[PDB]
Image (tube, rainbow over all chains, first blue to last red; front, side):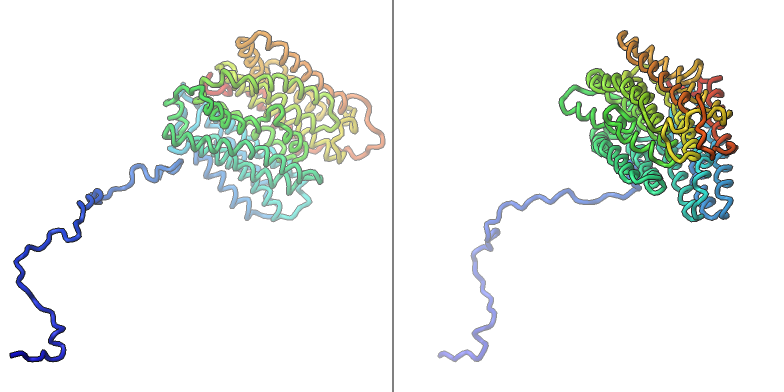
Amino acid sequence: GWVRPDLGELSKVTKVKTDRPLPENPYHSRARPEPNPEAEGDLKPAKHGSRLFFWTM
Amino acid sequence: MLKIIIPTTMLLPMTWMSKHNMIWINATVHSLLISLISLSLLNQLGENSLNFSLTFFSDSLSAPLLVLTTWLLPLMLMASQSHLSKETTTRKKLYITMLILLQLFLIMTFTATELILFYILFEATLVPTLIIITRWGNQTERLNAGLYFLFYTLAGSLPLLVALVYIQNTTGSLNFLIIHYWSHPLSNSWSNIFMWLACIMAFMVKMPLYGLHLWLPKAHVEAPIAGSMVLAAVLLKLGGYGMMRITTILNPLTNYMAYPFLMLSMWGMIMTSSICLRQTDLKSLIAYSSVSHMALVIVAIMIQTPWSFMGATALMIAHGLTSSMLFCLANTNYERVHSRTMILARGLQTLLPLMATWWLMASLTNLALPPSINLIGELFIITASFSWSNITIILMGMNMMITALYSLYMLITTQRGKYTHHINNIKASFTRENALMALHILPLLLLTLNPKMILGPLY
């Protein structure tokens, strides 16, 4: 009671119902680094202009 | 101070598109008007420097130099009229532009607020004079004159720049007001000595100081007359204005490392004055005289006494009016005789009556008759130096005696005696150079009446 699979039939993507749990860390990744302090806040004119030598503004 | 800056830069378009013959009249009249406007700067409060703007401030030290520059500018304008007649109009306007640009940089230098801004225009005066000395000079050596004058000042200028930017990173500001008000004692760490040094030789190379002065005889005797006055009258004093400024923070180091420069100077003027007595060129004497007179100023600043600072200021302004007069006086003789040899044209009183006077008190102000401001500056230095050390008195007292020795010597070897009979081109003394000397001398006696305006902020 066996039928030869047609062309491309054996190349299809199949689905299975394995009862093992999905490995949470397959790569055994270490703790991810904390992000650098986020850039936010409002922008206001530079205090006392360029502040470089004799340039008041 | 833009009430002086704006009209001064406005002299450029006016002098650059005036008529081919009105450039002298126009430049002279409005420069004098600027001088009158600059005269209002004589007002000073008790101790608060006039803080007109964030980037401009003045006190009783800057204004007398400020008026000196502005009052001076018409004087080379009239002095240069003689030997600039044989020139094209475009080049003539170029000459006027250099003088006005030199003036404009001078006013910004004295009125500067922080040291770095002061440094930029301070040095910036090298460019206009470099063109003046080299392009419009008279002899082959002027090419070697410019390089000697340029590198000498620059060689000391660059260390100051490194120290100045180092000030900004450490103290946090370079503004003079904050530096003096946030002044802190300077430690004697071996780095701090060079820190002290880098802020000094920049000012003393152009003073000039004994040893580091060779550019002075190689430039003033050799520059065009118009460049000669501004070099001697003000440009040397640029070290003085800076040194009173930079000394506000460089303490208490001055106690130790003043010595290697002090007796370098103290043996200096006596040595230089000896050279003045034994010159062969006319302008060489006044140039060597200028460093001799400048030498007592070096002692005045460095000793750090209020009396010396007043003496430093008075001698500074008095020497500028004097040295300009003698350089103008030498130019008058050089023009007719086409040389500057001292004994070439001795005995000209019989032919030059008014000149012989213009020799007379100009040398007497060089001898510093009482109560001319020359002594008022000079005597204050003496009292300050004596309070520092009693044995000082013999040295510069002997110097002002050898100063007296030569200061009549050209009077004897230019006016006293008999004319040279082969010379026959000493014409009638033109009113131009004649009136030039009047404008030199009358402010000296006028300031003698009320000297209280030129002792600086310490008065």
